[PDB]
Picture (cartoon, each protein chain N blue to C red):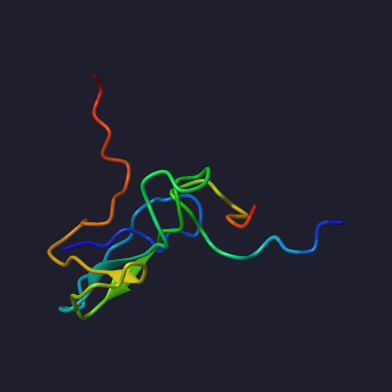
Length: 19
Length: 74
């Protein structure tokens, strides 16, 4: 159940960085 | 003078001509440490500190010092 899609950025394309 | 975007997702690069506005880099490891490289929430700051963060905000003024994709063909 997606409930965390706004954490941070990564090298360029890890929209959801954390996992 | 210029300073890439904050790295929200689609690195497009923004300007930064307010006098003091280097390009910092918020990273935890960088250089293969997960999947999308690593955290690197770029940004623009007016100060270029320096020390042994081991994981904090880096710095580099001048202009466009936070591109990231500097891969040349070949």
